[PDB]
Every structure is written in structure tokens, then in C-alpha cells.
Amino acid sequence: GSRQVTKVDCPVCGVNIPESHINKHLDSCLSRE
Ligand SMILES: [Zn+2]
């Protein structure tokens, strides 16, 4: 994916993942941990 991609922390559970995977993680985490 060496083109354009950022990774950030999950405000709910505190994990680092790419922009697509993190948005989904924190969305599902806002419900369950
Ligand atoms: Zn999460």
C-alpha cells in the first residue's frame, strides 16, 4: 500500500490501524469495547 494511506489510534480500545480499518474498528468499538 505504498501510495497514500495513514494509520491512527482507536479512541475507544487504543489500537493503531490504517484509515479504513480504524474507522470501522472505533465505530464497532463504540458499541463493544
Ligand atoms: Zn478498536
Image (cartoon, grey):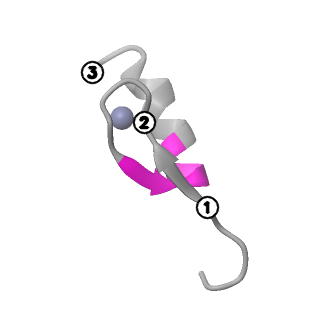
Near-viewer residue (9 or 18): 9
Q: Amino acid at mark 1?
A: Thr
Q: Quick one: quadrant of the C terminus?
A: top left
Q: Quick one: quadrant of the N terminus?
A: bottom right
In the image, the segment drawn in magenta is 16-22
Q: CA–CA distance between discs 2 and 1?
A: 13 Å
Q: CA–CA distance between discs 3 and 1?
A: 23 Å
Question: What is the residue that sits farthest to the right in this orientation?
Answer: 4
Confirm if mark 3 falls within 8 A of ligand 1: yes
Vertical placement of 3 versus 30: above or below? below
Q: Which mark is residue 10?
A: 2
Residue 2 in percent (x, y) is at: 62, 85
Vertical placement of 31 versus 25: above or below? above
Residue 24 in percent (x, y) is at: 52, 38
Q: Residue at x 71, y 82 (%)?
A: 3
Residue under pointer 3: 33
- Crowding at dot 1, Cα within 10 Å, few <14 / some 14-19 / many 20+, comes out as few
- Crowding at dot 3, Cα within 10 Å, few <14 / some 14-19 / many 20+, comes out as few
